[PDB]
Length: 193
Length: 193
Ligand SMILES: O=C(CCCC(F)(F)F)N1CCC(c2nc(-c3nccs3)no2)CC1
Ligand SMILES: O=C(CCCC(F)(F)F)N1CCC(c2nc(-c3nccs3)no2)CC1
Image 1 (spheres, rainbow over the protein chains, first blue to last red):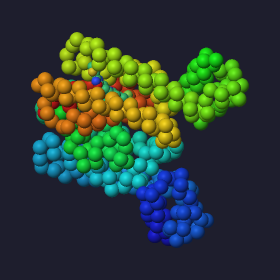
Image 2 (cartoon, each protein chain N blue to C red):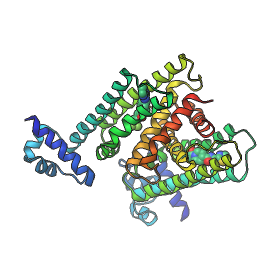
Image 3 (cartoon, helix red, strand yellow):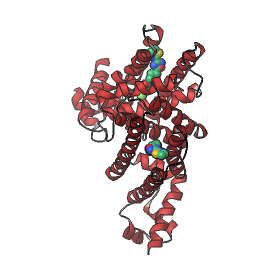
Image 4 (cartoon, helix red, strand yellow):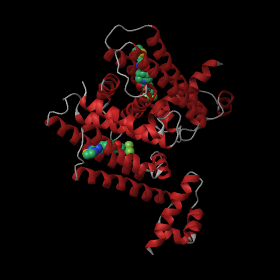
């Protein structure tokens, strides 16, 4: 019943390691999930709706991990705080590289994917901005750029850079270096200046 | 003779303001250029080869503008120097928004587009790294991150952010604010921490 939907999801994720969404067929997904093609369609309209659900669970998982951080303040310096937050995305998407990579490419192609990505990027920008402002009210950060324009560019940086790394793009920051790199840039641009 | 190739190029660029590459047909391009469909094919294999040539001229124009800067040192502070370099890309691609935007999307789809973008991103990263290092030998910049990993992430930032703005994406930095935003981040992350 439910367990089948989960099987279609797990099959899709497993096949996206080895190839793109284009070379995955509804029949491939049905086979893998141990159901037939017409049973597949009872659970999802398309292969693309499978991706969307997948991306949706990943992004929500990152989002939830970030709320947990926000509610339970990790006790530390400014540098470590920021690193902990960037680490949420680096870990969460880095554990779901095929879904990430495919979810990025379907932004060009799927309006729902584009808008889901958009909703969350906005949510995460807003929270980064809310935290930069909080940091400024306290006197820890100088009032340089508008907080929200700063948050925007720094979050756009992480998206490009994190996914470039994960995909192994030329050029990219090696994955083992990406986190320190992004953090140096967040911390100097937020506190400097 | 040559003037026709230029007409196909100018037609393509003009039609990409109003719609995507998908909704532009070879016949559309031929019409506009005042030639027939089989004459089109004498000059280009495909519509996609038209885009490539277009992207190639833009990217080379940015590249050339950056060399001019590099050879003739503008006399100024560290902040203005960097701003002048980022301004090359903001101006050059901002004058060619449809070609940019289309050239970004065809990266997913065209290996030649992907590799052209890749060659230049590498070239521009290398030069940013060479300049960060020069700045460090002089004692103006501290030896924090590896210069080349720093250049990489900052250049990835500009790509994402500049194009997000130009496309009017949600979310993005307003185009009238994008340059100051990127510069604050370059300068604090290069000189700070
Ligand atoms: O890196 C992303 C989004 C990246 C999304 C993506 F797509 F993967 F590129 N950040 C969004 C939020 C930002 C952030 N941390 C925090 C906090 N940490 C600890 C306590 S409060 N508050 O805000 C961390 C960077
Ligand atoms: O912004 C880009 C590439 C962006 C590419 C793109 F795709 F548009 F996002 N920069 C590459 C090079 C960097 C740079 N400036 C300079 C100099 N200025 C003055 C003298 S020497 N030396 O290096 C400027 C930022």
